[PDB]
Length: 87
Length: 413
Image (cartoon, rainbow over all chains, first blue to last red; front, side, top):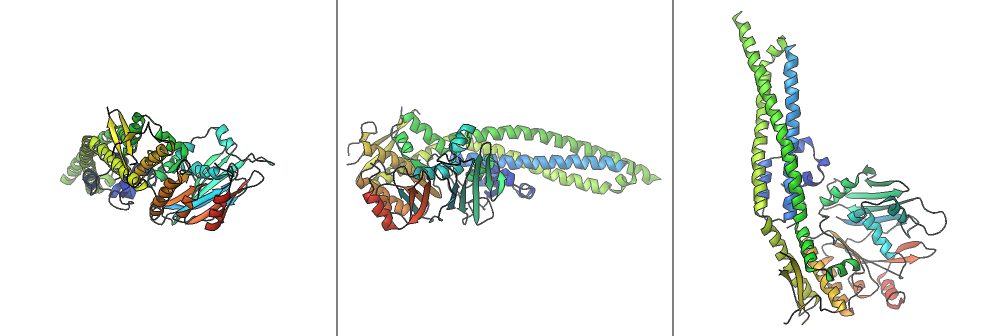
């Protein structure tokens, strides 16, 4: 109900985002599928405690925020590249 | 994950470098004369792992240095070496070391010899299952009494927080703040895609104007830019899917808020009855929800149950302990530290608590102290504290030395 799986499973990187997101890498953030992560939270094998779901919620939102961070960085860099190619 | 070894230096009575012999993964019991430094041994571990020692004023930091005799000490450290076989610590090592060093104006954690912050150590232990919401990874008499003599409202506040009400409301609020900050990045992202699309329209029609007949590089890479833009779009769409998934999640979590909490309460109560009946065979205990407003205990060591208020001494202590055991079994942990939790119990009830640790130690590590020989029966490895020259030492002893020492020691009650 509280510590499910010892992790390295499906919600593994979510759990890591929720606690020590320092150790969460750009490869992790990119390959994280937010919708199957949410799906295994809203209906898990065993019902999980409000504490665990609270962490995981922040896990999912933190990865989602990092996807935006990279997409923004990349869009600014793609827009600069086009302006530069004009000249 | 268990505590494999402890090293102490300069901490309270442990002036000298004390390399404690590596613990058994099961039950380790520490015995020694009253005031020889056994509680100091648990403080040294709590100094590294417990969040109540995380913030130390400089005066509090200094009071942990050894002030025993001669060259008054200017630095201390304690080092926990974890076994990390079951890879519960998010660190790809079989052994993880965590040292905290203090000095006059130094207070530094080290993870495998590399400096880390206090938040790092908190998050490191949180992701291994050690919840700041659970006050019972260390149990002392102070906690047992605090439980036994607590208002029913306090029992409720504690169980609510363990169930996760405070954690959840805090993560919910930080999530929201993140969503709205992200909500700005998504707009700026859509702006830039509109600006890029603009230049792709400019480009295409300069490109067309030349075919009837701006650097050639932009014209050369026109198809490259258009291909790149769709790769950005697909990622932008991934964000929009994710936003929808989060909204569902937040909504579903909020709608299951109470049945989550109610399921944690039903579990603790079910455990409280089971734990107690096993410690007091032919007894009945259960939690009661009041006016919600509070949580009370009703127990019968016999079919007519009395309350915690009108209960004996070493019975209030046993019942409170039984409740703590239930919460533990409900939010379990890889290792436990018991500082004389058998202190206020009858010989019979110490024997039952000893029988329970025997079975628990099959699945978690225990590091305990006692001055009564019941708990020595459930132990797997034995340590004795010796105190001479106001300096604590700790050494492995045999079971017979432990049982003999405890039997004819006069220093305790």
